[PDB]
Image (cartoon, rainbow, N blue to C red; front, side):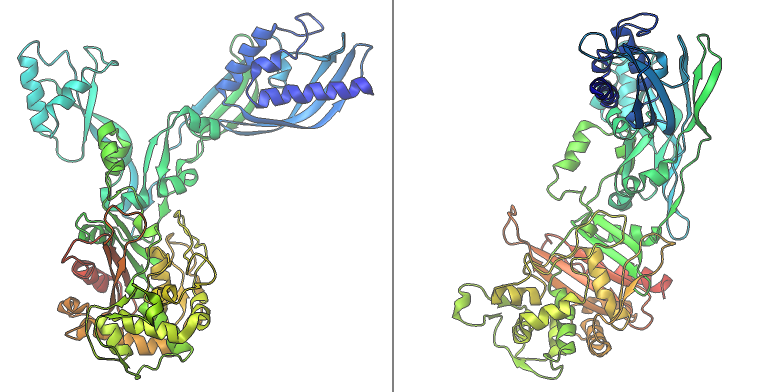
Length: 640
């Protein structure tokens, strides 16, 4: 019994050494090379495991049903089931067997080639054949491609056929000026270490018509991932990059020769898009004829993925941001279909996946506006656009009388002297302010007062009926919205600020469109939906239908009234309810006093489209309302 328990420990440490990939440590637990002992030396066992397990990308070896008995006075037989993960799937229900040797005071393994794979004998070989799976496409709600695998026009040069002296310099300047390339970039490419004189050195992917080819220029058709919307959908879709050996160590089922999604939807849906590798893992005799087939299945190409995105709305929404920092979200608020998820500024996902320089990537990574940020998934203060929610809550619990008129004198206001230097500010000095007036002029002081009159308890009661703290069911990495840091404001200042959408509020543009959808569904919140086939989810009685039929008529006036903050949109001549907003930028910040401009807008007749646009760190005289005219036309025309 004392020796049977020591033999079990030896098998477990041996298996553990194999699972950890330390084949040397596993071989030093085997007995001497002999006929009834081990079949190979220690360094020969090392190389056989490293070659075979390394070829099939074996990972995660674990055992079960371990039985160790006794066969002779120095021989103990052992057996166990085992499973492992390879580049072709899981190897389940493997029956291993062997013998132990208890000479001396230690117990070792009589190593045999059947401890690599069960039915292996002597000088048996292992063969792995694999067929790459094609990555699936990403398409919009109408079948238009957002991420597809296609053929690209690879522009490159061959240094030998270029010239000797002077003729080589004339063609490099000719190819650099004919394909929009630096004259230094072409010479640095043809002078890298990997280059030989007769090689084809790639340069650029030509995404259009190919111009005249100077001496030495040539185009070669290659296959790769292509993004038709380019930067307009870069943050949402993402990009794919070459697969590294580290990626294979984490997941052997990837193709060492394939592409993996590095960010965005390409990464969120990497498993469904990459498919599964096909092929066969077989054991052969010492010459090359199959004994047993361990794993085999045919190649399965990746599934396509259809989004609620409209490829035309996505492009217009992005272009309307004019390269400035901001984001735009468009939905069909009755169902939650995300028509557009635009973030700006952006990067080139085609240049990103088809080889990007160190400096072009460093330009993206060190831009202060940070184009890599998915701004539709980043928590912001919602801005004074948040009056609608505070007002709707105020009408529900009766704190707000729509016809009661507060008297506000000036542009600054504070409750009392204990606020010190803090004051609630408004842009328009209107003396007599009712609810309809406050929404038309975006009067933060009216909102700040009604919030204090409502109190924290009644305010949170109305706020909690929304989606604060909830994780949305979306394939987009995001954090849940929050009312504040803690469960109590514990500050009349923070309470008043949260009233008109400042404070510690944090709501990303997608979560905003979900919260604001109550005004298109009579108080029912419609959760947003990105995958086209998913079922529409909702949350009823978020705000009262009374509050909706009170506020939406006022939100029309924000567009129609000549002093409405969104009056520039009445030029469209379409049924519009809107609300503008502003918010102060917090955090460290390289410039302390910077503002964010918000715009919410939807069709109050058909409830067919909804829009939430923002402009981070806005330039002067710029606003989200100036830029929304184009997207509003398209959404009004195509989504009734």
